[PDB]
Image: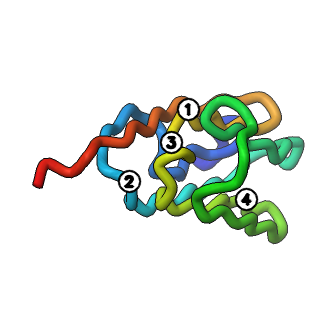
């Protein structure tokens, strides 16, 4: 057993979470089909640069490492891959301190 479809959801990103800005999240993806296309969407729409973002491509391993340090970068993160979609919602919650 191993195949499931395009892009394996080995990403700690697939749910609604509300937390203060500064939460580090790493997306790990292992695609079953190489036809997978690399295409990420920010806050649902391509905005300006804010949070730290880096691309790591090597063979079939496709992983985007993003650190939520910018509040402005908060928004809908939809990860597309060939023929698959990911649903995640980041909300900035002021400290309860």
Q: How far across and down, in percent of the image, does residue 42 sit?
A: 66, 40
Residue, far right: 35
The mark lying in front, picked from 4 and 2, is 2
- Per the model, the C-alpha gap separating discs 1 and 3 is 7 Å
Horizontal side of residue 91 vs 41, given as left or right = left
User: Colour scheme in the image?
Assistant: rainbow
Sequence-wise, which precedes: disc 3 or disc 4? 4
- Compared with 85, 67 (above or below) is below
- Cβ–Cβ under 8 Å for marks 4 and 2: no
Residue positioned 53% across, 30% down in the render: 87
- Per the model, the C-alpha gap separating discs 3 and 4 is 22 Å
The residue tagged with tag 2: helix, strand or loop?
loop
The mark lying in front, picked from 4 and 1, is 1
**Disc 1 residue crowd, few under 14, some 14–19, many 20+, Cα 10 Å:** some
Q: How far across and down, in percent of the image, does residue 62 sit?
A: 73, 59
- Cβ–Cβ under 8 Å for marks 2 and 1: no
Residue, far left: 97
Sequence-wise, which precedes: disc 4 or disc 1? 4
- Per the model, the C-alpha gap separating discs 2 and 1 is 15 Å
Residue positioned 81% across, 70% down in the render: 58
Sequence-wise, which precedes: disc 3 or disc 2? 2
Residue placed under numbered mark 3 in the picture: 74
Disc number at residue 76? 1
**Disc 2 residue crowd, few under 14, some 14–19, many 20+, Cα 10 Å:** many
The mark lying in front, picked from 2 and 1, is 2
- Cβ–Cβ under 8 Å for marks 3 and 2: yes
In the rendered image, which quarter is residue 45 located in? top right
Horizontal side of residue 65 vs 97, given as left or right = right
Q: How far across and down, in percent of the image, does residue 66 sit?
A: 58, 60
């Amino acid at each position: 057993m191993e195949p499931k479809g395009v892009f394996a959801k080995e990403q700690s990103v697939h749910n609604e979470v509300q937390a203060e800005a500064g939460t580090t999240a790493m997306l790990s993806c292992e695609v079953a089909q190489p036809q997978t296309e690399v295409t990420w969407y920010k806050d649902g729409k391509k905005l300006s640069s804010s949070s730290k973002v880096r691309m790591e491509v090597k063979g079939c391993t496709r992983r985007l490492v993003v650190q939520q340090v910018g509040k402005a970068d908060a928004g809908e993160y939809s990860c597309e891959a060939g023929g698959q979609r990911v649903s995640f919602q980041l909300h900035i919650t002021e400290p309860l301190e």
